[PDB]
Image (tube, grey):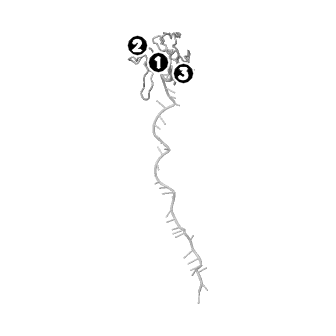
Amino acid sequence: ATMGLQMVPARIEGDNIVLYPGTSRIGNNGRPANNDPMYAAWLPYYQNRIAYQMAEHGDHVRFWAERYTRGNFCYWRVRQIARHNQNLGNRPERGRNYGQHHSTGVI
RNA sequence: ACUGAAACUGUAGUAGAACCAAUCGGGGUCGUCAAUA
């Protein structure tokens, strides 16, 4: 399970692989550097669902996210989502502390 | 401006001599499987 911390979200575009570390930056060992947040954002899906019907693996999307903290690390908790062509709407605010997933209000 | 008649294509000969349906294999035994929070 340690090895997952040095995986990066990726795609292939035509015939090149692409990487999407996004706002996070790739640390030397491949881990997200300097305690910056996980490369991918986290979508609540089987509990505290962030609904638009629930999105699906092919969905191209636009979304708000919030920086959340847990223990040794932090991550972009998705807050609200729309299909890409649709309007995302207004900025959400200070989410619930979902237990040890603590809000920051950094959105 | 008088059909020739009569005559067994049969008589003797072992489709056989030689060759392995066989060569190798313990009815045996350990750590995997799924990916995140």
Residue A22: image location, x then y, percent: 43, 18
Q: Position of residue B36 (x, y in %)?
A: 50, 17
Q: Which residue is mark 1?
A: A40
Three-letter amino acid code at the position of disc 3: Ala
Q: Which residue in the rendered view is the most extreme toward the left?
A: A28
Q: Is residue A102 above or below residue A6?
A: above
Say which residue label 2 marks. Answer: A34
Q: Which residue is mark 3?
A: A55
Q: Disc 3 sits on a residue from what chain?
A: A
Q: Are marks 2 and 1 in contact (CB under 8 Å)?
A: no
User: Which residue is at the front of the view, A81 or B37?
Assistant: A81
Residue A44, image x, y percentages: 53, 16
- Dot 1 amino acid type: Ala
Give the label, 1 or 3, closer to the camera: 3
Counting residues from the N terminus, which is met first, the one under dot 2 or under dot 1?
Answer: 2
- Note whether B7 is above or below B31 in the view shown: below
Residue in view at x 54 percent, y 21 percent: A55
Q: Earlier in the sequence, mark 2 or mark 3?
A: 2
Alpha carbon separation for disc pair 2 and 3: 32 Å
Q: In terms of depth relative to the viewer, which is nearer, A52 or A10?
A: A52
Q: Earlier in the sequence, mark 1 or mark 3?
A: 1
The chain to which mark 1 is attached is A
* Residue in the foreground of this view, choosing between A27 and B35: A27
